[PDB]
Image 1 (tube, each protein chain N blue to C red):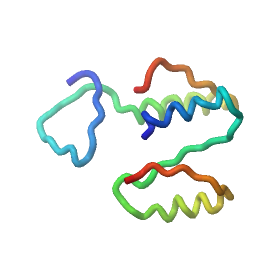
Image 2: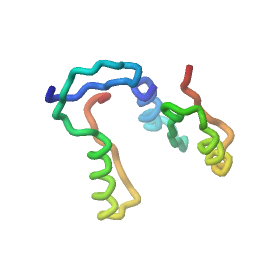
Image 3: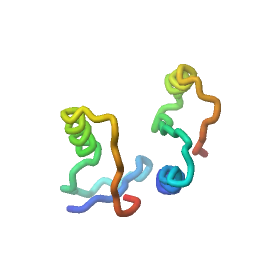
Length: 51
Length: 50
């Protein structure tokens, strides 16, 4: 997904969006710390690459 | 082996040896470098995907 995401990563040549990046847990399914982090992050528009 | 290739986890061979350096070590090196530089602006310059 990073290979097919880097286009959107460099795409703010055209636009001024703010954009961060995080990873799912690579082996575990306890993403609940990350979700706690994004709850602290006060964001409302999140990209999801997954099965 | 000498160069690098991506290797997944379910990818489960046994018989291999490489000498390419691990990327996370390299990014850690650049991390402590720019932390020795203490910057707030950055700019990614690169050729391709990898």
